[PDB]
Amino acid sequence: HSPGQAFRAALAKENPLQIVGAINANHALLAQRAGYQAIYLSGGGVAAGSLGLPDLGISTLDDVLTDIRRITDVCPLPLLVDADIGFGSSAFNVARTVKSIAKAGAAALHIEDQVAIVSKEEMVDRIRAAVDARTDPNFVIMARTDALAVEGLEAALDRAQAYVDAGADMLFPEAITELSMYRRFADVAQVPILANITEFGATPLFTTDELRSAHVAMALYPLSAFRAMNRAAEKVYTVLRQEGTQKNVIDIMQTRNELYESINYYQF
Amino acid sequence: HSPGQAFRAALAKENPLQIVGAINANHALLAQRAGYQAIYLSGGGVAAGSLGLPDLGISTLDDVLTDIRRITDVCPLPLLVDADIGFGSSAFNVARTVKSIAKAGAAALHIEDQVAIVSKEEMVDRIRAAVDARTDPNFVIMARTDALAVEGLEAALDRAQAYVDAGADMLFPEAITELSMYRRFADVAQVPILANITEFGATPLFTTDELRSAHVAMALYPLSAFRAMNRAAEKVYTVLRQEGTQKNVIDIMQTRNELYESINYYQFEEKLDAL
Amino acid sequence: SPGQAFRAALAKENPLQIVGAINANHALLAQRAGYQAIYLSGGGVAAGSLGLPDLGISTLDDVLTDIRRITDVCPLPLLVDADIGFGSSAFNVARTVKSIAKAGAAALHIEDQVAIVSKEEMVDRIRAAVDARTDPNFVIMARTDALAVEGLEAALDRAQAYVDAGADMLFPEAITELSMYRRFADVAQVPILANITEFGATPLFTTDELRSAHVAMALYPLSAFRAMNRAAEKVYTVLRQEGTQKNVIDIMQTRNELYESINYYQFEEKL
Amino acid sequence: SPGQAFRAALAKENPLQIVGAINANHALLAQRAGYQAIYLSGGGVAAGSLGLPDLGISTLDDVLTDIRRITDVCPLPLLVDADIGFGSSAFNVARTVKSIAKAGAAALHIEDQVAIVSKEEMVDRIRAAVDARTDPNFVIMARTDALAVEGLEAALDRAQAYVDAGADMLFPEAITELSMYRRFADVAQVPILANITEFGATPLFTTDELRSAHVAMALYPLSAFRAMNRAAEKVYTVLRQEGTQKNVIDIMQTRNELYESINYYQFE
Ligand SMILES: [Mg+2]
Ligand SMILES: [Mg+2]
Ligand SMILES: [Mg+2]
Ligand SMILES: [Mg+2]
């Protein structure tokens, strides 16, 4: 079996492929039961959820690898991972990172040019080191760029093909506000484009149909479920503390039968 | 500063002391913000939450340690930990488990007498191996008994005495259904009594006022937040999968500002501004 | 496929010398010395990585850490001592087998240790490991001590049963005569591993002698480790006694040798 | 507390010999040999535990694992090589410092390497490390290679700034004269550590010599490790060339010596 294959196959059977972030192994199983073909391990989520830390580069590759093992050990859905800038700097750092992640169970990962961003060149080597470190060719190397917002469209598209020439299997344009931009990246890069549809950002809540008219090959929802899980956990804590009992929040609680079924308790 | 001292100080300041489970570091910080004085690491939660596996002894000590460090590295609230039966059928194991758990940052832990449960003489030896291994005396060793699920109250009360004698700092009487049962353990054990007020169990949803009348020292809610977290998560998944958009789910989502405040984001930025 | 590389080493070298590597650095020294397969001793993980006696105190986690460190830098197929599966439940053996393979190992062995469990008990453990296996090339070796315990009659029977159960190779403990390995090889009908550790009961059989015995693998679990400790103790002692390490400089690997062994310049080249 | 134990060891021995222990087993050997403090070499974690060069490839997690393994079984206070803090920001330094203490370390040293950062940058790393520390007895050592990179003046200027910033002790590199060590001790006014590693440009100073130079600590980072690698290689080569280890039996630690060092019989 090859998670890299499963991922590439998912984008093939679903367009745009809906990829939802799963904060932990339990939610990965839920996402599966909901019919999702692929999941995501958000870097911001590992920091905020697993570590209770802001997304300021305090988490480490190890924190990330732990969640990949937990998730991919029980959930077979191909897992797309946020590998940031490689957590290292040199070629062997990017390589060790890419191999670690793949070995942990990932199906794909994405590295970004955000140092402002790095030069086209340096990002080109970063991608080469990533592609070179890859053992399974089906493993997906995604290149995330923020050049559009930094250097402008022209420079953005230039990097696009540059990154693709280096071997990036897919592109991840960040902070896009207009579908047009997606079609352009698709027309130039000519590789599966990913639309990050996260909430409370500068991007509109595009629907799968809208994203399709723009040629988007993947629709990402990084923290969607996490944001809802926090609001509900907070409600439980709040009510329990005020009322001295959780009686009035039982109705918003997943039942046992539900928990057991989501984790195949009975089966064991 | 000791976490064990913090746990004990929490008890003296809140009676009964509400101890809520936090499935991860983020929720621990939420619990702290909600005003709680102590938190809990559920073994069933590590299994089902962190591993997505059933609570059937599949999780290892390492899975637990990882969650203990993550939680206690960012949240100062004393953490009570479910050490199951000691992770290891050997006395050596129990000792290494106790020391490792404390080192990971826990303030307390509870070890149980399950094998059906083991005999008194048996449980008494596990308790002794744990108290022996403990380096910091303030670190709490709570003794949990599941006798009430297959035995009568009297039988359960008997063990309670033997457990305390071995060195058990506190008692965790499982499956109690009558307020008076708590009172009897409190009067026989002579040490703080914890009441597991988890949902969908044989134990009624007793209120803090009810438990207080029964002389209960701690009120435990092991997976409460976790259960509501799962439902809401699923809701988002289902809708997003049916309507190809999360638009109709925005209203039940924690806002960016709320997320940032819970993890002290602005505070980190402040320190940078300072430089 | 690490399992595929392990089987190819078996076919290429007969008997195949499998030396223990206490850590990633020694795995590279072994590789540079020409070895085709290495070993991760469970007794090594306890005494070396944890400083604890080999009495069941280490956990699967301690072992997975060493497997990753070793396989993340050394490509040689690694045979791992998995004891009895770490746990007691078929779920534990399966989770252990998968974990070990995922960590990067090429093979592992499990024993009928509880006195030894019953044949049926072991057979189930083996079946559990074989079914948990994802890569059919990943090797599952069955270690047994039936000979000493229950005698040859029962031992030879367990052997066949283990093989019928799915064991790719056999690791029969307590053998002191080549004629006995020969017998075990004929019965089992799968590669036999001979444990040539020192300070034990088994003679220090040579690769030639083992070959004449139909032995497929020669294992040296702690050999390098034993020597590294005596040398280390020597440095600690002299330095403490004399207030300088001047007189032990001659038994030390130089910095150039260390750099060379880990390919220092090829990395700095990338940088 | 380990920090208390480290300072107690320093108070009772002059200079305090601190030998590196590559793993838990060697920590125990150092202990049986009479040492009162041991060290976890950063280059040792890389070359020994990871089989990689000391070029910034190891992560904080690799170091932490070794600290726990060693300190869980050996009570001798452990001085840890925290490199530059395993991160670029003060947040990384704080997380690194707390994690290392939590793992069981008694003290750590952080350096000004990047070329070296400006005096001001190092002053900030130290301040973050000092602020992150929860137990004042836990030692924060400042390591500097400014002597070789910038010269005497810059080195002494940095030293004083480092002490003013909160560094409990100083680890000045590249000193080749006992007389210069005295100068650093006099200007810095905090315990000075002298690195007596082999095959470098520095002399193999005896403890009596270091004492005359007012040196408070003598460090032997990989001494045992070096000898262990030569012996191990010897076994590997002879066994490969002769087809048996009969001829290297005489350089092997016996089963009883091993059992004795790990207290086998006691557990039994
Ligand atoms: Mg990210
Ligand atoms: Mg439990
Ligand atoms: Mg073994
Ligand atoms: Mg270093």
Image (cartoon, coloured by chain):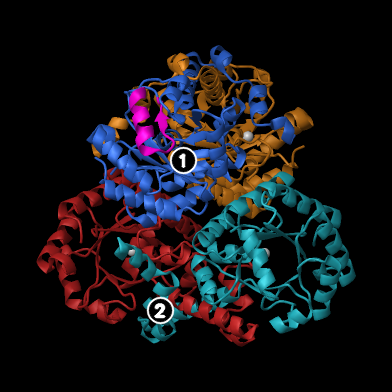
Chain colours: A red, B cyan, C orange, D blue
Name the element at disc 2: helix
Q: Give the magenta range.
A: D178-197
The chain holding disc 2 is B
What's the CA distance linking mark 2 and mark 1?
A: 50 Å
Check the picture and name the quadrant holding the C terminus of chain A: bottom right
Q: What amino acid is labelled 1 in the image?
A: Val
* Front position in the image: B104 or D126: D126
Q: What amino acid is labelled 2 in the image?
A: Arg
Circle 2 residue: B241
Picture residue at 63% right of the left edge, 40% below the top: C83
In the rendered structure, does residue D185 fall within the stretch colored magenta?
Answer: yes
- Image position of B128 (left or right of C171): right
Do the residues marked 2 and 1 share a common chain?
no
Picture residue at 36% right of the left edge, 28% below the top: D181
Question: Marks 2 and 1: which is nearer the front?
Answer: 1
Q: Position of residue B213 (x, y in %)?
A: 78, 82
Circle 1 residue: D80
Q: Up-down: is D63 above or below D205?
A: below
* Front position in the image: C14 or D257: D257
Q: Which mark is residue A51?
A: none
